[PDB]
Length: 245
Length: 245
Image 1 (tube, rainbow over the protein chains, first blue to last red):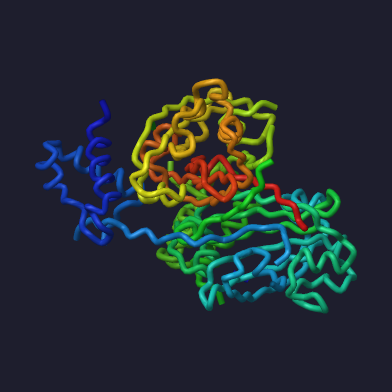
Image 2: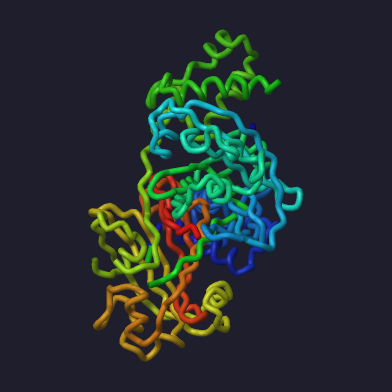
């Protein structure tokens, strides 16, 4: 890294049976032949009913078709407030119960148009790019690429995120050390197939979907850091807690 | 609804060319034969390089392979604060610039284990289930299923979300009308293939991924509403704005 249509009727009935537990995970879906006879449908209808359930990710192959066991999702807790002790891991996963570690690599770069725009600087202007692999008790479960404008951090003790007196303590603490007060954060959660490099690092198969948080920290209206934070969609959800006023 | 491996090296080079614009959307990816000759690789290596880019969703077929045009994503703005005027649409899409409409259908039900748990009531206890289809200027772009405990709304003027004196004004306003003050909201964003019924309503193809927000409104520690809010991952991102303290 560094009158419903027949096939929907049939599919609907089996889907219910799947949600019931009537068809428990690792149990074979009724066969094509069985679906045809039991529901009195054509071969194509039985075939298309099965394709619905597969496109929906409810069943898979592994000589027959098996109800998939879908894991209970874990939350990646998102927060702007201060923790116990601040680290890049705790900054991404606010859940105090989770003990976590990271490896990172930092190197300068000229900002792409896209990153320049997220940081509100001229394209080609220099940034510090740091990549992280985060582990939860030895298990890799999150990736991140973070960009910071050298206009802000250049020639300061916090220029390198994982070095110096506040290295390893995250963006808000590192910024505060140079009299820059982060006061807002925007986070946009999207989903897409993982990049090979991401999926290989995260241990998923090609085509596996990841959640991608585009995150930008602000100090007095100016962007001071932007990042793409990546977690496997099959295992995780991105959790927010908001006030209602 | 109601030393990198060869194929990664090659794939990496073409991916860069794709990000460059060197290979613009709707332009054919170099052919298998061209990749073999230009990069001096085996047929299988050229083949596997192409599969990386397809699993990554960067290229597609449509007699050759074409660089996909990936649309600029739109934000679904998430917020707990009060808007102009409150509606179920504005409750889901805080972005004031977006003019939107909905159709809904409400009917009682016994709470499933899963919904019972999200609402902190006994399974089988009755709820009002309301389904929404939301449109942005005539275009369907969001689905939702909302459950409310009849323990809270039963025998009140806000029992039916889209009827009565505060019907069509959303959960926080409807709850306030019955002296129930919603003070917190939790939102967990996940991703999964859409259900046929969802994708058919949203206009996607089978297997298309949706973002699913599991949302629960709280009043004084008690859940008063829970919902699954659904948007197409290819077109939308879920946007949050958080304070940093």
